[PDB]
Amino acid sequence: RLPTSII
Amino acid sequence: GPIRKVLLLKEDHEGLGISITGGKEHGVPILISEIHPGQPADRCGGLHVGDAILAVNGVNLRDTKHKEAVTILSQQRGEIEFEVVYV
């Protein structure tokens, strides 16, 4: 449901 | 918890060293979900999994959508100030 981004 | 200001030092060849979740379109804050070992966020000592990122270098992130936050966060260079809170 929730996006994850590696930054 | 208390709102904290935390300084992070990043070199130009590296990322921040975090994973973020959430965003306004999901009704939740930008949250740190991972601190990658040895990368700038880990090294700075003051950022942790579960912290909500309220602002970076004075830019409010409390109402940003996920991808807005990614763009803003990834633009920051050098000595970067975070405003965060662990709830």
Image (cartoon, coloured by chain):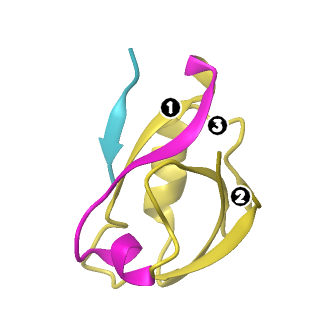
Chain colours: A cyan, B yellow
Question: Both on one chain, marks 3 and 1?
Answer: yes
Part of the protein shown in magenta? B26-44
Question: Label 3, label 2: how many angstroms apart (C-alpha)?
Answer: 10 Å
Name which of mark 3 and mark 1 comes first in the sequence.
1
**Image position, residue A3 (x, y; %):** 37, 27
Left or right: residue B15 versus residue B47 is left
Left or right: residue B42 versus residue B27 is left
Amino acid at circle 2:
Val
Which of the 4 image quadrants contains residue B15? bottom left
Checking the image for residue B62, the label placed there is none
Q: Residue at 43% across / 59% down in the picture?
A: B74
Identify the chain of the residue marked 3, using the numbered disc in the image: B
Amino acid at circle 1:
Gly
Identify the chain of the residue marked 2, using the numbered disc in the image: B
Name which of mark 1 and mark 2 comes first in the sequence.
1
Checking the image for residue B64, the label placed there is 3
SS state under label 1: strand
Question: Label 3, label 1: how many angstroms apart (C-alpha)?
Answer: 9 Å
Q: Quick check: B76 above or below B25?
A: below
The residue labelled by disc 1 is: B22
Identify the chain of the residue marked 1, using the numbered disc in the image: B
| Other residues around mark 2 within 10 Å, as few (<14) / some (14–19) / many (≥20) | some
Q: Residue at 71% across / 58% down in the picture?
A: B59
Question: Label 1, label 2: how many angstroms apart (C-alpha)?
Answer: 17 Å
Mark 1 near mark 2, Cβ–Cβ under 8 Å? no
Q: Quick check: B11 above or below B30?
A: below
SS state under label 3: loop
Which of the 4 image quadrants contains residue B84? bottom right
B56 falls in the magenta region: no
